[PDB]
Length: 109
Image (cartoon, rainbow, N blue to C red):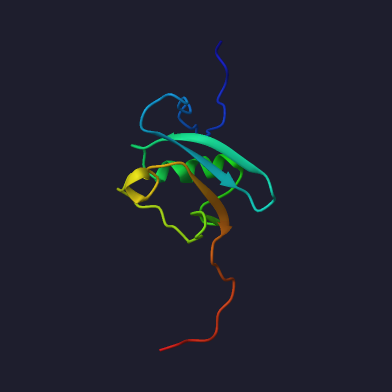
């Protein structure tokens, strides 16, 4: 079983169980209409989310994670846990298009 030099690809940590403690149920809502649901410990860091997004086929620099109604543009925190930011209980996320611009000209003071 000695394969040549394969490509490099990231991998997500085996999803937790339904009985596992300190575990919530997060679901990502795609702009296409489909919705994926998965569990995630309450100790993990929002950061892990960014990785899960790149797996489904979406980039962070292209989309962002938002909360449910009231909907609000959330921004991962390099240090705060999922439950620390506000993911202590089952919540629903909505992958929205990040605010970008491929132009310039006007300048405000």
